[PDB]
Length: 134
Ligand SMILES: CCOC(=O)c1c(NC(=O)[C@H]2CCCC[C@H]2C(=O)O)sc(C(N)=O)c1C
Image (cartoon, rainbow, N blue to C red; front, side, top):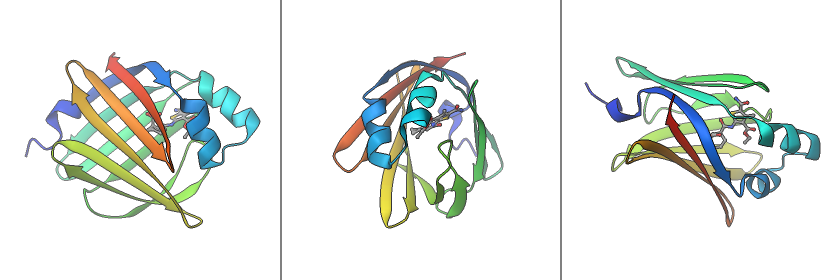
């Protein structure tokens, strides 16, 4: 159904801005911030029917989520939070909200030119992570 076609593929992280501050706000501790911050994950996005799968593979961690748009699921994040996640499409942007411990963060993923741009926000702190095709 050509849902998410432009996101599908294998992507490599090529830049990150303000990620340490984002992680601090989320509650990531020092050692994990330092080692996570070094990671340059491959993000692999695929679609099969209504099910979207997003894998992230790096030297630090491999993560995988599979979901249906609009349908909440329990996610264990790379930093080991146990969150309730809901991912929707809003105007062509994948919007991923994570809830845990009365906290919330929002991750937006967009296609912009040949890049996939990820913006993540925790209170007033935004980080931008830019991926290119692998
Ligand atoms: C919050 C701490 O995150 C990490 O350290 C981190 C990942 N975070 C993400 O996949 C999301 C982070 C929030 C934005 C969306 C995502 C993005 O990075 O693009 S994957 C990963 C790995 N495979 O090793 C690590 C180490």
